[PDB]
Image (cartoon, coloured by chain):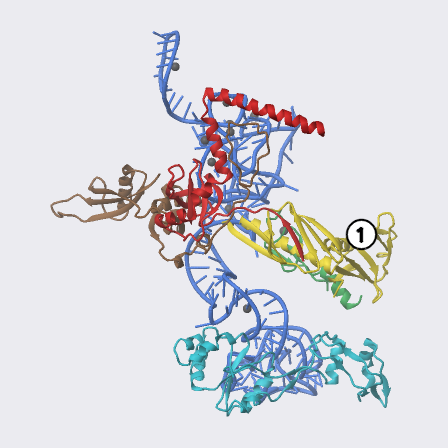
Chain colours: A brown, B cyan, C green, D red, E yellow, F blue
Amino acid sequence: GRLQEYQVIGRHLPTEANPNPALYRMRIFAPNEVVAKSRFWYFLRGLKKVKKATGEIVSVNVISEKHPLKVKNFGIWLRYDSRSGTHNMYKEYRETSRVAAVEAMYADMAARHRARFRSIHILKVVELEKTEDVKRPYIKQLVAKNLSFPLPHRVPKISTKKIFSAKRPSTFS
Amino acid sequence: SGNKAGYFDKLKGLLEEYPSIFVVSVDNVSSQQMHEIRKALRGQGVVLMGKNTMVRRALKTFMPDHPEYERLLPFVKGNVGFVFTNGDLKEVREKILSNRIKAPARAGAIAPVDVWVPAGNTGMEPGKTSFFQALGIPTKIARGTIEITTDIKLVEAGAKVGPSEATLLNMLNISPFTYGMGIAQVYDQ
Amino acid sequence: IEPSLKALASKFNCDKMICRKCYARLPPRATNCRKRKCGHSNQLRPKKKLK
Amino acid sequence: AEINVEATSWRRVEVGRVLKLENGSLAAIVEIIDHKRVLADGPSSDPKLATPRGIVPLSRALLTPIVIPKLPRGARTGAVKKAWEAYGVDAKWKETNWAKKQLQQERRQSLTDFDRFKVMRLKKQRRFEERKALAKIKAAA
Amino acid sequence: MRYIHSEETIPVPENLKVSIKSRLVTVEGPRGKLQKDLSHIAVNFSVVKKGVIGLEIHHGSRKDVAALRTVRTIINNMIIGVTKGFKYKMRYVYAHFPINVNVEKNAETGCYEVEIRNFIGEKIVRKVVMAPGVEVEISKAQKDELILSGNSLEAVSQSAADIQQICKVRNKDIRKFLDGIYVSEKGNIVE
RNA sequence: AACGCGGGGUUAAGGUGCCGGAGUGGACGCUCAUCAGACACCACAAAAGGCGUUAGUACAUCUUGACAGCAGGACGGUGGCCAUGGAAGUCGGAAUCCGCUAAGGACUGUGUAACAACUCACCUGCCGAAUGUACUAGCCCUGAAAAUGGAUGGCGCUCAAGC
Ligand SMILES: [K+]
Ligand SMILES: [K+]
Ligand SMILES: [K+]
Ligand SMILES: [Mg+2]
Ligand SMILES: [Mg+2]
Ligand SMILES: [Mg+2]
Ligand SMILES: [Mg+2]
Ligand SMILES: [Mg+2]
Ligand SMILES: [Mg+2]
Ligand SMILES: [Mg+2]
Ligand SMILES: [Mg+2]
Ligand SMILES: [Mg+2]
Ligand SMILES: [Zn+2]
C-alpha cells in the first residue's frame, strides 16, 4: 500500500508559431499524485526541451491491476548508480501485481547493493507469459512440478507480557 | 561440425537406399580388424556407424518412409552399429564374423575360462628363469630349453592375472581373449 | 636407498608448493594458500628441487 | 536387513491442505507463492468458518490434518466450493481436538456470576463421590 | 539463495542392521559394533525403501548443504568397516642406521604399544600407544613392513599417522635426509 | 528552540532490551570477524589483494549427449624430402598430402646408439544436465606497530540489542 502506478500526460504550452503541441505519456510509480507529477517533469526534462514553467499537465489517472488474484512472474529492467559509475541490471520477481513487484525491487536493491530510491531508473516492467521465459534459478525452483515442503523448527507465538512460563515450549507446530 | 553435418545426410541417404539393414555390436575391437574387414568388403556392402543416435533416426521416423523404423527405437543402447549390403541374410550370417583376432592379456584382465599350461618343452633360452622363480614355479633346463615337468595352474577362472603371469602368457602366445564382431537381432528376424 | 622407497619418501617432503607471502607448505595442485594471515593468496611457486 | 529410524514427521504445505487462521477461520491452499506466502480461500457455509480469497502469510497459520484430495492447482472459487462440500470439510473439522478445545474455552468465558456460584456447588457434589471411591481403592492398596 | 530440498540415499546390505535414535547412529554387523553421534548437524533421517536410508535438508543455505554428502560418506564407511574392515600398511625408509621396531600387547588396558629404536642412530627410545580396537603386527611377507587393521577407519588412520609423525629429522635438509616410516597402501581386510 | 508566577493538552531535535520515561513492535534481505559492528559536526585510516559469501555484465560449449572420473583404441606410403658408426616424430636445418572412418601427427612428452614400448594429442565405450573464461560492486577478511589498567557512555548483544 506504499506505491501506486499512474498515467501522466503532459504538453508544452501552446504558442502562435506552434498551436496544438505534441502530447507525451509516461507510467510512474509513486506514493501519491503530488510526487507523481514531480517525477514526470524530472524524466521529461532529460528527453525533450520542456520545463514545468513552460508546460502544463493534461491528465492524471490511476492504473489498477486487472487480476489481483492470479500469481504471476515479472521481469524488470533498471539502471542505477553505484559509488563509482552506472550500470544496467535485470531481475525477476513472483507476486500478484505490478505494484507488488516494484515494491519488492526497491527493498531488494537497498539490501544487496545499498542503492537508494534517488539513484534508480525503471526502464520496463513485463509479465512473463510462458514458463520457458524464466531465467533466474531462484524463481525456477518455485515453478517446479508438484511442489511441497514442511516447516521445521517453528517457534510458537507467546505474548510478550507473559513472563515466567511453567513449562518448556516445543517447536513442532 | 562439418563432418557431423555430413554424417547426417550420409545416414539419411544410406538407410533409405539400402533396404537390408543389419545390426552389429562391436565392443573393444582394435583398428586393424576394422581395416581388414573394410578393405575385404569395400567392393560389396558398406560398414559404417558412429555415436549413438537418439533423434537422428527419429528424424527418419517422422516421415513414414519406413513404419518399421519406429519399432527399432528401443533397440539401440550404445556402441552398436548398422550394416548396409545388397546380399542375403544367410550370406551375411557369417560374412562379417571372419578374421577373429587373438588379444593378449592387459596385466590384470579377467580370464572368463580357466587357463592351464600343458606339460611340454618350451624351447627357449633358460636365461629368463628369473620370471619362473619369481612365482616359484618348478622348471627344468633340458637341452638348453625350459620344460615344465608338472602341470601348474596359472589362474582361477574369473580371477585377475599378475603382471609376471601376464608376461609369461604373452611369451607363451596362449590366451582365451578372442575378439570379433558380436551379432544382434536384425529386423525382429 | 632403493629407488621406489626414495620416491615414496619424497612424496611427503619434496613435491609441494610454497606460498610466496608466508612460506607455507601447500599441496602440489593448490591454487590458494590455506592460511588466513596472508588472506588466502594465490601467488605460489614450486618447492625447489635438490640437484 | 533391519533398519530402525525414529525421527520427526511434519505436515507439509501443499495444494489441498486446510489451514487454521488466527480468528478461528479456515482456508484451503490453492497456490504456493514463496516459502512464506500462499494463496488460499475457504468457501464455507458457516459464517464463522469462512474466509475470502487472498494471500495468507504462513507465520500466522496452523496446519490441520485435513487434505482435500485431487484439488487442481489454481482452481477458482466455484471449483473449490464444490470439492469442499463433497469431501465434508465442516464435519471433519468438528471432530478434531482443536475444535473441542475452542468450544470449551468459549463456554467458560460466557459464565455469569450466578453460573459461577452454581458450578462451584455442582463440583463439590461430584467431588464427594470421588473422595469416597479413592479412599476405598487406596485402602485395599 | 536458499535451496528448498536436498537429498541423499544410502543402501544397506542384508547382513547387518542400523539404528537411529536422536541422531545417534549404531551399526551392527558380522565383525562388531560401531557408534557415532551427529547431534551437531540439523538433518532428517527416514526409511526410503526396504533397505535404503534417506537424508534430507530443508530450506538449507549453500554452507549448510555442503555437509549432507559428508554425513553420507561417514556412515557409509561405518557400514564397510563393520562388514569388511580396513587395513593400512607402512614401510621403513633409511639410508645408514637401521630402524628397530618392537610391538607388545599390554594386559591391563588391552591396547598395543610400539617402540622405535635407532632412528638416525639416536639413543632416545620412542613409544606410541595405539587406539583401542586397532591391532598391529610385523609383516612376514616382506621386510620392513608394518600392518594395522581394525573396524574404524578413523581409529586405524589416526594411529598410523601417530607413528609417521613421531619420526622426524630436525636441523637438517629434509630433501637429503629421507629417513622415517611412511604409509604406502590402503585397503580392506577382506579382498 | 530563545525565558514573568502556576494548572491541563500537543509536539520539535532526539529516542522506546536494562541503567531510563516509551516496542525484546511489524515486512524483505545482507553479515560469522582467534582485531566483528553499532549514527552528522567528532574525536582517523590508504594504495594493493581473497576459489569467504551474495547479486550482476559479456563471450563461448552442451540432450545431434557438454565439464569430472573410469574404460578401450590410437592405422600405409612415411625411417618424409636432408643430415648419420648411429636419429624410425622427439641431436640437429627447413615444409606440412590423401585412402580409413565417428577416429590417430610425415607428432606434445618419457624412451632406444637407432628400433621398440609407453604415450600423448585425437577419437570412442559409461553417465545423465548443465559447464568454462574474463569482468562489475555490496558485507566480511589480509594490509593494521607504543609506552599506568579502560572504554560503541556502561552492562551486554549473533534469523541481533549489527548494516
Ligand atoms: K523482533
Ligand atoms: K567479492
Ligand atoms: K548511546
Ligand atoms: Mg646445517
Ligand atoms: Mg506543561
Ligand atoms: Mg526504532
Ligand atoms: Mg521502562
Ligand atoms: Mg579496496
Ligand atoms: Mg568429456
Ligand atoms: Mg569513557
Ligand atoms: Mg539500545
Ligand atoms: Mg534495522
Ligand atoms: Zn600464504
Q: Badge 1, how many Cα within 10 Å: few under 14, some, many 20+?
A: many
* Residue drawn at (43%, 35%) of the image: D23
- Answer yes or no: disc 1 within 8 Å of ligand 4: no
- Seen in the picture, residue D105 relative to E64 is either above or below; the reply is above
- Observer able to see residue E22: yes
Q: Who is closer to the viewer here, B147 or E40?
A: E40
Image quadrant holding the N terminus of chain A, namely top left
Task: Identify the residue at image location x=74%, y=84%.
Answer: B171
* Tag 1 residue: E130
On the rendered structure, is E138 left or right of B43?
A: right
x, y percentage for residue E69?
A: 61, 55
Q: Nearer the viewer, residue B41 or D132?
A: D132
Question: Residue, x 80% and y 60% (percent of image)?
Answer: E147
**Residue F7: % across, % down:** 39, 10
Which residue is at the front of the view, E121 or E73? E73
At label 1, the amino acid type is Met
Q: Quadrant of ligand 9?
A: bottom right
Residue C50: which quarter of the image?
bottom right
Q: Is residue C40 visible?
A: no
Chain name for mark 1:
E
Horizontal arrangement in the rendering, residue D136 relative to residue B132 (left or right): left
Label 1 SS: loop
Residue E174 location (% of width, % of height): 76, 57
Q: Position of residue A51 (x, y in %)?
A: 23, 42
Q: Quadrant of residue B31?
A: bottom right
Is A92 or A14 nearer to us in this picture?
A92
